Image (cartoon, rainbow, N blue to C red):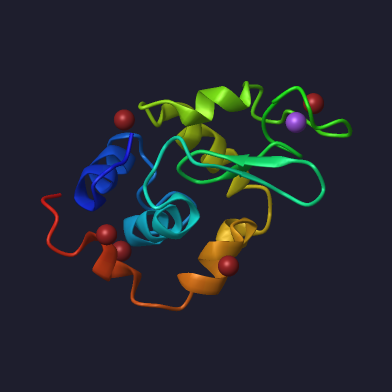
Length: 129
Ligand SMILES: [Br-]
Ligand SMILES: [Br-]
Ligand SMILES: [Br-]
Ligand SMILES: [Br-]
Ligand SMILES: [Br-]
Ligand code: NA
């Protein structure tokens, strides 16, 4: 599923991601934009053999199981395919675990490089929340 900007913001708010660990809704929408372009089916392989999955490109090296990342962990205890669903629940629950791991949203390199320090409120500007 390819979300609309305000549609995703609404969905993220519903699952309690807005202001989670102090990160406002615009930070999460912006992260999604640059990680996946709002596409829940996005996948990307990394040089180390692991793979990033879903709307927030969650990495199989640590967080999910995809059956082909040898040294990896499954810290959210899910198949990586669950992060590709139309329904963003698994992605939101896993992101909440990631953002609490110590490094905040810096875990997402696109957030750090393309959202951090910017006017992230723009990403939910105009939405009915
Ligand atoms: Br957009
Ligand atoms: Br594996
Ligand atoms: Br949803
Ligand atoms: Br980047
Ligand atoms: Br915001
Ligand atoms: Na894994």
